[PDB]
Image (cartoon, rainbow, N blue to C red; front, side, top):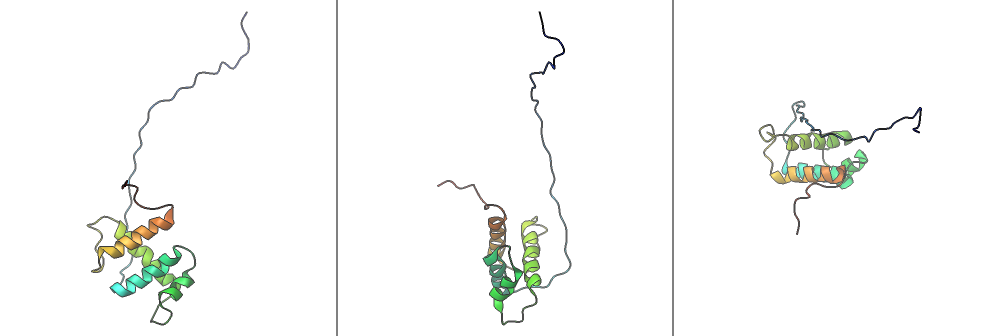
Length: 122
């Protein structure tokens, strides 16, 4: 007395599996050297807004100096960020302090998703 024409579903098990991946590299056009002051203000302009309107960047940065263009500033930061994030041997930018790379990197991640760190546990 058994059933007929049934699906006979299995228990459905799970097997182990690994995962592999690889980073990426690149190179942009030839840029020009910047000043600690110009970079500081420039970074603060794009950082102050994180990733919204470039107009506020050019205005916040310095609406008086010999600025270039909204996108110019935004793009400038993005580029410096990639170079400050890439490998050390490849990170051969202008003679600037690590702070610049720390502010651009930290901010980039801060506005990215959540933040950068999760290592310290006071």
